[PDB]
Amino acid sequence: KPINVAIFGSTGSIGTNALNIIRECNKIENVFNVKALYVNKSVNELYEQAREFLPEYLCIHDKSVYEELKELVKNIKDYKPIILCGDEGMKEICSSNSIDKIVIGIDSFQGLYSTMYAIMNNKIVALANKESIVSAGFFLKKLLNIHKNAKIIPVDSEHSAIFQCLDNNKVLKTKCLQDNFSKINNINKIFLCSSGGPFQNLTMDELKNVTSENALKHPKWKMGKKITIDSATMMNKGLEVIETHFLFDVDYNDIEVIVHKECIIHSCVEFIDKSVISQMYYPDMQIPILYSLTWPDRIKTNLKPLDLAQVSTLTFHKPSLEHFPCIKLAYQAGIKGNFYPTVLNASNEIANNLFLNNKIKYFDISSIISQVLESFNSQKVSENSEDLMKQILQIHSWAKDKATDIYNKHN
Amino acid sequence: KPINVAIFGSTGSIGTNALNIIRECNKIENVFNVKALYVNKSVNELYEQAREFLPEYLCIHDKSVYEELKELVKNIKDYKPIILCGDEGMKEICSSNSIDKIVIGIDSFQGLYSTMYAIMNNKIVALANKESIVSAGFFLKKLLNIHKNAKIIPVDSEHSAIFQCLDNNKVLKTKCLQDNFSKINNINKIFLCSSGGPFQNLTMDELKNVTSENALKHPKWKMGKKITIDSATMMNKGLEVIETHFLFDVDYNDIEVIVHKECIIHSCVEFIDKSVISQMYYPDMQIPILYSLTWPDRIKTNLKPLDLAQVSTLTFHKPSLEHFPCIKLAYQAGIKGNFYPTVLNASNEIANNLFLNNKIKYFDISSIISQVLESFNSQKVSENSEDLMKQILQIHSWAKDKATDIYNKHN
Ligand SMILES: NC(=O)C1=CN([C@@H]2O[C@H](COP(=O)(O)OP(=O)(O)OC[C@H]3O[C@@H](n4cnc5c(N)ncnc54)[C@H](OP(=O)(O)O)[C@@H]3O)[C@@H](O)[C@H]2O)C=CC1
Ligand SMILES: NC(=O)C1=CN([C@@H]2O[C@H](COP(=O)(O)OP(=O)(O)OC[C@H]3O[C@@H](n4cnc5c(N)ncnc54)[C@H](OP(=O)(O)O)[C@@H]3O)[C@@H](O)[C@H]2O)C=CC1
Ligand SMILES: CCCCCCOc1ccc([C@H](SCC(=O)N(C)O)P(=O)(O)O)cc1
Ligand SMILES: CCCCCCOc1ccc([C@H](SCC(=O)N(C)O)P(=O)(O)O)cc1
Ligand SMILES: [Mn+2]
Ligand SMILES: [Mn+2]
């Protein structure tokens, strides 16, 4: 009974890590079939992955490299995949009855589109992309209410940890990103752990002048550029607070960010009796990815065992909101609700990219995001799913444009 | 739907803590009926508990204070309990259809008797007593195989932690102290945490001359004298290694003792994928006791919330087997199997009591236990439950006598 999986964003950090744990898992016993691979424009790298995994489907988003892809794959003998392009290609893969689970390793708001179509096709969605949940949580909840057999299984490491800390006897009565989830699961409060990022010990004077080169250098594992910058600003953790709220139905007052620099405890769940359960491992994404594909079971691996005497010390401290103002902006946006999380995500996408490209300074990131949030006024939420998606898109686009306009003006 | 509970050993540390969380839990909403209280000889204290809780049944083990108990309880107006004595009284309570769950807070090998009769009556046994499991694990397993609806739910804090870390979706397919439990639950390895006791930082020269007064002073919560001495020698943790083996069907090579002096992580479970799940709270017995009575659910409490920034640091180190030789003796006994754990428990009961009463020195404890273990020869295991109990009793008694004889001889 092999598990038929598609990897969306297969050439990025998540996608390559997913293919690695799959490869390793299969050597112990052949449990996964890699049925589809989808990328944006990394045509040479997708070709190489195609030669190794020989999926039934290949898809490339950028039309300008589709012909190139076909020409390359011609060089793989005895291999006749279905080779698709763009939105229509993604939709065709999601509607295939040969695919059971889809790993969403596409970055940014863009990952919402495939997330939505995977749910609409009643698939198990092993969701790493958090911008989708932040920007469109209420929408996704409505979609999941309609598509009974669709499920989001969280891959983001902290949310995987939380999910692993739950009793599946209770989980199986509901599913993530549903009303009443915390009540059913007896959840009282979440400790959302953070690495703290590379800037965690810097002074205010030092933060003023940090660069994106400083944020990107010497990663534990290479993550994509966007998340790496968000880790440095701790906007990642702000996004993950909102993600927690939506996935697990936890009030913002019951989500506490804790800086745990060793990254061994990945997050913790306090139940209503005050007992706390936590998930622990070395800093890795292989367990989150694997668990999303095996849940509700676990399978044998040969991963390096955790050794607590080796670790020796685990530390916890609260983050400074003066140093990391993005965290507070995320809580404020989440608490306001409505489309404020959409605005938060969109403005951050622009500010993150500006800092990445050395156009603005560290504290300008939070300044831009704050100004966009203050400029937004709540809208009535469309009652129809199609209109609600259009409204999310329009607000996301406006907020990106507003961020860019603020940048353009101070120049 | 109140939960009908008996408290065995109601005047001791476990028993009084059980009555405290019950009392507190009932204020939030009335979920427990205290149906029976049983003690050895603490007749005045049992009377006081009777006046507060007004259980249907009262039992006192020591015949010489039974009349006194009756005379005292006469002073409680409008109260006509059933007042029993000894083994026959315990058996009558265990066979009552009005009792659903029994907390076993009786110390030492003596706690085996009520444990056995609670299982024979198909009850939920909230078992704090570990000497029963160490001395008679294979026997209890056979009994639990026959008595389908009987269950041991562990109360010992580390074993409660382990149990809490399991997925009830899998637990409910089996029960503790059963063959194949680890396979069903996907358990690979256990981290068995320890406080390390009051002697953890002493040198060999200092250990030579430690006293029982040193071991007993200034407890976090007052525990009984026997367990307190076993914590000081780390024989408690040796006993708990064997307890882990039997409760959870974990090989001794897959049980690792770790000294965690802050006592926040109560123990950890490594699953076959290498993910680790742990349970955390302040050092307390209220959660273990409560969970044993609410499992498979959890209920609301108003316990002090865990605060990780307050805790700040968690530490882990391996215990020194030179300083704490009892640990190694326990592993050796467990690995040999047969009745060696019975012998280990019995010899320790004598050696612990000798040290408590200032008759022997610290390293004489392990010396006596080691000599008794070396003197024992494996026996064929009786095939009949009744004969098997007689054989356990005979070996336990011999091993106590052998320990005392070794003491008597070196004097
Ligand atoms: N990296 C990590 O360990 C973690 C990541 N995440 C989340 O996972 C997501 C992915 O992050 P990460 O892997 O770091 O990002 P990367 O930048 O490393 O990878 C992004 C991937 O998405 C592909 N992609 C981009 N646009 C499209 C498109 N329109 N259609 C199809 N594929 C597309 C890229 O293709 P191409 O190569 O062709 O450009 C690439 O394969 C993010 O949402 C992030 O927050 C969460 C937890 C940790
Ligand atoms: N204290 C703790 O926090 C922990 C304890 N445990 C285990 O729990 C058990 C109890 O320990 P603890 O509470 O510390 O011990 P205590 O010495 O504090 O209490 C023992 C209790 O058992 C009663 N008792 C003794 N013999 C009999 C008998 N024949 N019939 C009925 N009752 C009897 C005693 O009655 P009386 O008062 O009349 O003498 C007393 O109520 C031990 O097996 C220990 O290992 C495990 C984890 C932690
Ligand atoms: C050896 C110790 C140092 C390990 C450092 C490597 O581990 C991490 C772990 C987490 C993260 C977070 S960003 C990525 C993410 O969201 N994930 C993995 O779920 P954040 O900084 O926001 O908490 C970054 C690095
Ligand atoms: C504030 C930090 C200091 C807390 C010290 C108080 O907590 C503990 C916790 C555990 C124990 C063990 S003996 C009792 C027992 O078996 N339990 C509770 O399950 P051991 O020493 O064998 O690990 C003793 C004391
Ligand atoms: Mn994360
Ligand atoms: Mn214990």
Image (spheres, coloured by chain):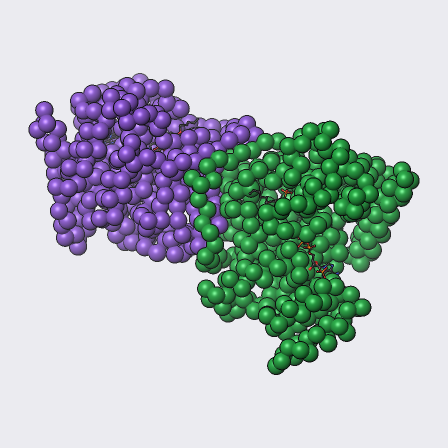
Chain colours: A purple, B green
Name, please, the residue furthest toward the bottom: B78
Find residue A153 and report its horizontal and vertical position in percent: 37, 43
B207, above or below B172, in the image: above
Q: Residue at x 56, y 50 (%)?
A: B284
B119, above or below A325, in the image: below
Q: Please tell me which residue lies in front, A89 or B29.
A: B29
- Is residue B96 shown left or right of residue A358? right
- Is residue B219 shown left or right of residue B206? left
Name, please, the residue furthest toward the left: A409
- Give the position of the C terminus of chain A as an image quadrant: top left
Q: Please tell me which residue lies in front, A186 or A370.
A: A370
Residue B328 visible in the snapshot: no
Q: Quadrant of residue B162?
A: top right
Find residue B236 and report its horizontal and vertical position in percent: 68, 43
Q: Please tell me which residue lies in front, A180 or B221.
A: B221
Q: Quadrant of residue B72?
A: bottom right
Q: Residue at x 47, y 54 (%)?
A: B303
Find residue A190 and report its horizontal and vertical position in percent: 39, 46
Find residue A326 and report its horizontal and vertical position in percent: 26, 35
Q: Residue at x 37, y 37 (%)?
A: A318
A270, above or below A81, in the image: below
A405, above or below B409, in the image: above
Residue A273 visible in the snapshot: yes
Q: Please tell me which residue lies in front, A404 or A224.
A: A404
Tag count: 0
Q: Residue at x 59, y 47 (%)?
A: B220
